[PDB]
Image 1 (cartoon, each protein chain N blue to C red):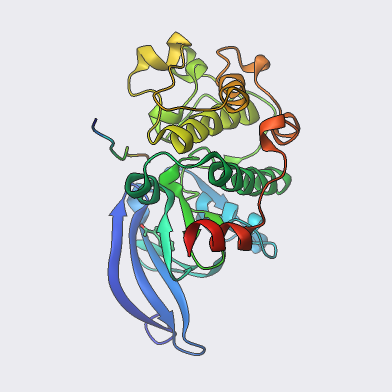
Image 2 (image 1 turned 120 degrees about the horizontal axis):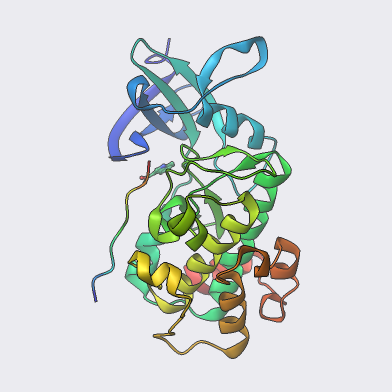
Length: 273
Length: 9
């Protein structure tokens, strides 16, 4: 039974990702988040061990649930007549990166470096496990404020990672690459790198660079905040119009702007506590 | 300048 293993709390929010409640696992008072997804809204389905048919989101979370990482951990799930219920780990205290940037404004580069580094490791983890997130954005990043650790959430737009072209997309348009806008085609890793350029600009300038299709495809990055030349270069490299001109994850993490990152605990003590 | 969330899914 699901209502006897967890005490359900207030609604945290709802959207294209379903409805998410705060919760507590009764056995050990572990804080959890309880996500409800309507079966009629699930576009992509998968099968797991023993071929049980589940939402792709459950398949993807199981593949990245391996151990500890910068990804939200799926603890359990249940099928109901018209929905699936997902039990997720819940950091406390927590704030998502969108609200954080709204309240702080443009982040100091030392802080953006630490956050961006942890997002890179998280996305590398997903790709290592065969999972493409397809919706990297500040809204989909939780900050564990006491530990200074970032966690990726909301895999409901993701897919199994492949090397052939993708022709479907349900992530966030203002983070999607110009080859999607123009041709409704993209490849996984290069599209992910584009969204990471959007995210890095978002961090160091206080908001995303583009709102309209014409801006996404136009290929001009105007900096609205003082940003070091090394960071501008990395951003512009990630936002190369031609996908093959974008850096690999290795080239991002080897970029001069990315060196000497703070540890998560240092990040919390210096910038979050 | 208006900063806003954007839907997905």
